[PDB]
Length: 122
Length: 122
Ligand SMILES: Cc1cc2nc3c(=O)[nH]c(=O)nc-3n(C[C@H](O)[C@H](O)[C@H](O)COP(=O)(O)O)c2cc1C
Ligand SMILES: Cc1cc2nc3c(=O)[nH]c(=O)nc-3n(C[C@H](O)[C@H](O)[C@H](O)COP(=O)(O)O)c2cc1C
Image 1 (cartoon, each protein chain N blue to C red):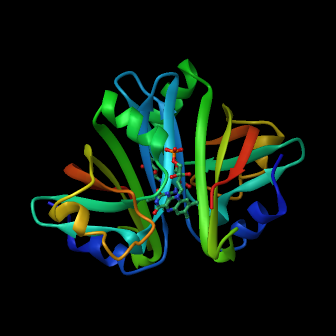
Image 2: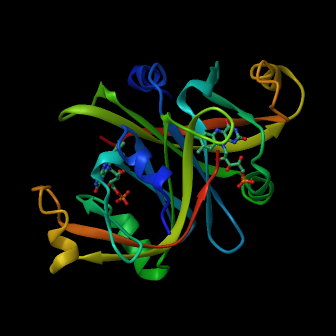
């Protein structure tokens, strides 16, 4: 589900954005490119320190959107590219998916996104 | 209301994310940090090439969220910071606000976000 170009982006630093559906409109939070841990089976795991509004939103609608990119990775028509990722989210406080990011001692949980599509948008 | 630290982020490379309310959940698109033009009156202007889905969403609900950041600007507790911006959006296709993105020959419109709040989230 995730292409090589996406993994090239992860080698470079940047701001990842994660959108959820809130009660009165969207919500949007961030993690660093370098924090994403990709597992077998199309899973992206990120360390959760805060994300309290985000978790409440996911509890009611598991569908999330994620974007990320880098000026340092070539797109289709010039330098720089990025991705829109769609997937279903779940929060874990134990298990192997949590342990994948437990090295971040500030992490109260892991946000696990199982990817349903990845589009290179540049 | 945009703080100095926000303008420092704009001096650095990054991916900006813009969330809108869609009919069946959020939508999320990107521009580059360096593309943003800030005008007086709390206005952030970005070049529109695609964003047809985003524009349709704005037509139904003008409220948007924006995040951006940089590892190269110090946050409150270490290197790296970023912002959550909330504001109202409009799409201009003539006039001063459109002229503000004139350097982008590929642009079909200017997305003008009038900022209601800016929160440094790291
Ligand atoms: C560049 C950047 C990186 C961030 N990385 C994380 C992160 O790895 N984990 C986290 O929980 N919050 C991170 N945050 C903070 C979140 O964006 C968000 O503000 C916070 O978790 C509160 O989430 P909520 O609004 O859903 O309650 C980061 C913020 C920025 C600007
Ligand atoms: C790093 C990056 C920068 C982008 N910059 C722009 C931009 O300046 N203007 C634009 O219209 N689309 C830009 N895009 C594409 C948008 O994110 C989006 O995919 C496209 O405009 C279609 O919008 P829509 O899904 O709302 O129709 C960029 C994408 C990436 C990954």
